[PDB]
Each structure stands twice: as structure tokens, then as C-alpha cells.
Length: 448
Image (cartoon, rainbow, N blue to C red; front, top):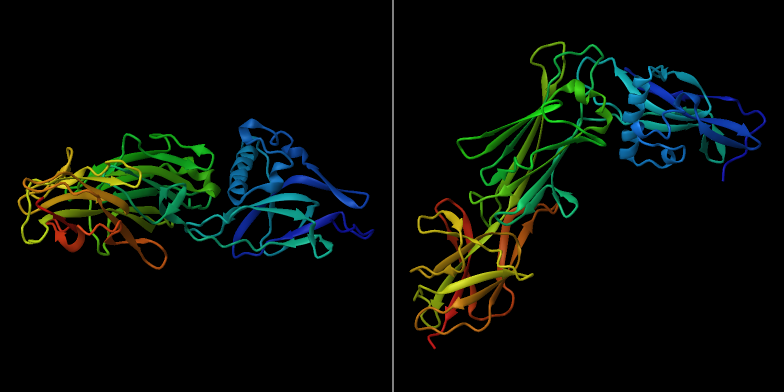
């Protein structure tokens, strides 16, 4: 595999790191030593007690050779902590210049910016000196690191994926995850703010029993030490939640960022529609100190996700007089599985309430089953209205959720009869007074 080592191979190499005005530290992880016609690696003396240590991640010589992007970050946080704890130090590297170093394997992390404003740390780098290049060893490695911009992103976590949009039933949990950049500053820096404001719309009930789980990779921060959670239910029905941090407590974990895990539940105030609409929204905002040397110097970040749900009416009707609207018919709704999970309806006042058993058709022919996500749904007649027979087969509708060109839900939906039952028929929608919109499955009943 590896190229031969020349006789005129130097015992020294170099790292050059081009930047505008930030200094990097390089930590010798492993020595590379010439032996015959190959470089043998072994752990450096300074980190003998860092390696294979349970308080610093049980990193072996071999395990650092196959770190994922996230694990290189986690490794850097744990190396930093060791170096601090043991009052050691890496080599400071001059910006733009050649830096002479022994042959080895190196962590390179940002030590500073010369900027006063909030910086994002460049992601940590593991580099071999020398490294293979063509069929030769390069002893003089150059690294231009990625110039990182601030991250704030919110996602719904569903089925072990992360998506900007979703659909659920009323009563179901929407789970959330927020990743964020932790800003870095110069060493003297004071009165640093790092503050989240999460805003949930009226349709979502924050699960404060479950609460927040706040994490930077491996680390689990403690409530009322590292952060506080204040919750304010607004007049308009929105919940505003504040997650405010002691910056000093998260500073040592800057390279692994902040992760928030929290969840809400879909409630009866939910926006229900079948046109493109805003849905049931979670907004996240991060405010943080920009220039700590000037007061009221902040930068803002925002993300949002949204969650949709749908509904339909039944309109029960006579076979040959479609204008004759039948009271007293009783309906149930099952999914693909066979759960009667459909258990929310509108009442006579026009407000969403839990449905006790069957949907009973009112004097205008109507019962409703609202707050359903997309899927196959089986409308079965459980009781025939007086003077009518039981419908034999269930009417099946498939509600299909519209996507935009990135495959986000838009909030639009279509409905169709899907099991070919000629008694079922899709008619014009039901417009509720709260401005929610339901599908309308017209269903014909014969009088014997």
C-alpha cells in the first residue's frame, strides 16, 4: 500500500494553515517513526494517560483512525478537557506561515479569532504528517479549513428521520430536535447571552412533563445549572418557551454544538384544512451576543417546522332523493391497521370535541371525523337510520397529502373513494366557522 521512504526523507515535516486572523492549536496524537521502509505509529507520551481512559472517551490508537465527522468533534471536546485538566498545551500554529512539526498524527483545532464579534469555530481536523499523495509522502501539508457559518435548524423527528414537515392525528405526539452552533469569542469575553425562544401555535400542547433534553454530543446538561426553561401560554393560544443558557457552562463543548430534544401533542385547537396553509407550527429563535464589547449587540437566527392534519364529513343521504338528508345514521372509521383511532368530531356549537363512540348524523345528514393524517380510511355504517337498511360494504376513502417540490407537506390534500363503493361519493367541502375545512364523503342509503 504505502510508498517507500527515500534515503533523503526528512525526519521533520510542516503544517501550513491559511486564514484571515485566527490561530490554531495542533496536538500531537501519535508519533510516526521510520522503521525499515515504513512509518510505524504509536501514541505520544503526553497523551499516554488520555488514551484508553474512561473519563475521556476510551479512545484507542486504532479508534481515532476511523472517526465519523461527529466523533472527531466529540474527540476534540474530550481532548481539550484533558489538556485543560492536566495543564498541558498543544503547538500554536502561525497563520499563513509554514510551521515545523515532528512526524505524526495531529488534531488541529481553532484557538482564537482576532475578531471581536461572535465567531463559529472551524470544525476540528485530523491530519497525518507526512500524508500519502500520489505515490509519495508529502511532508509539508497545507490545510484550508471550511469557513463555518452559524447553524440553527429545527426538525420534526419521525420514524428515525428528520423532516421539516409532518402529519399526525389529534392526540399524537410531534417530536422535535434543534441543532445549533455555539458561538465562540475572545478569551476575556463577558456578559455572553445564548438564548432560545421557541414558539408553538395554539394547535400544539408543549409536553412539559417530558420537558427538554439538552445535549452537546456525549454531554447532558442539567436544568437550573446550565440552562433554564420558562414557559408562557399566550392570550392568543400560542405557547412561548424560553431556553436560556449559562454560556460559560457550554463553552468547553463548542465544537459539538447544542442539541435540544422536546415534543408537543396535537390538540383540539389544531388547524385542519385541505388547501395549502401554514398548519400547526413550531418556531425556534436563537438570540446570542455578537460583539460582547458593545451592549445590545446581538445576532438572531430563526427556523420553523409545521405539522398538518385533515378531516372529513359524512353526508348521509337517500338513494334516489339525494336532497333528502338522513338523521340518526351511525358511522365508525378505521385505518389500514383496524384501529378505531378516529375519535374527534365537531359539535353543534362548532367546536372540536372527543367522540364517544359512533359518529351520529345530525338533521342535515352530517357527522364528522376530524384530526386525521393521510392514509386509507374505512367508513363503515354501524347503524342504519330509521326506515333504511344497513349498507353492506364500508366506503373506503384515501386522503393523499400534497407535497411541494422538496417533498414538504404543503397542507393541501385530496380525497377519493378507493374501494369502488358506488354508495360513496366525494362532494364539496364542509367549511367550519373557525375556518377549518373538511372533505365531504356523500353516502347513499336505500329504504329497504
